[PDB]
Image (tube, rainbow, N blue to C red; front, top):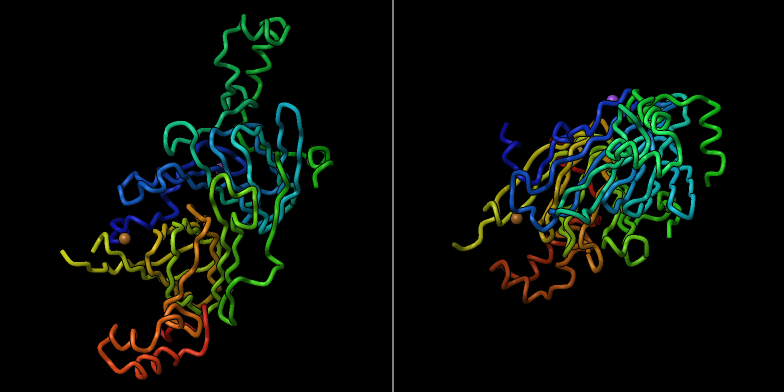
Length: 370
Ligand SMILES: [Cu+2]
Ligand code: NA
């Protein structure tokens, strides 16, 4: 109800399936400007989810957006067909893959039991925010784009009698994500290991961490394959009963999707808030929900109880972004002098400092008893 009026919150139900598939789904959030011009700064970007059931195959297609795939759950093989090169990669949880726009891909989940789930960021190259799929594979369902060509053109192009080529493009009726056999799975992923492979930071030391949570990020400073989009991929885990201390991002807007657990968030927004007033922008986040955190906006997340709270965040305008913590042992006030603190709060500087030093921990701490 009220949460339908928080323009930064995109509940999971707002993701729209692009097709009706038996063995998975592909669902995409509307353009970010659908309900608010406050998100015009990220209009070119879309987020989506791909889900493959066990023993499933997503048919060959390309998109007209530059993408970043992040594996959230399971294992799957991506096969990429370019004009002059083939690549296949066996992806696992935490893998990040930059996929060039126009790359023809297919996906395979070889596992017998576990779903394969990918969170995707795409950026348009045609009309702003418009990202479309082009099924080369297919027939009647999904419709293959080859059916847009006249039969004489297909005959001449394929050097194949028109009735035979037209028949080829009518056989598939099962949809875009279908069953795959054990032998097909073997064959397709047999060679899997411009288009570089995935990277994975799961085993690295976090950038920021404590006993209550972890943050690590793939930045374009480090990963050249993210530089063109100027994107980052952030992984944040808040342990059960924890919170991330209030912080803000200096320049990067974040598109945060919940992968595990639940949290309460509170954000300070001057836009929705004449002299400045900060609107209290609040809600709850569940698995599959998205929150957009505009740059500069103070935010906190508080894990709510029975689970860790885990998110993947895409960062837009990521180069040169820095996290600025607003409480904790390591925070911005560490770099503000005592006299400036005294003037800031109209109280003795040593007293301000005493209060600001009470929190001995950094980054993530125990949340409120609630
Ligand atoms: Cu704002
Ligand atoms: Na489905």
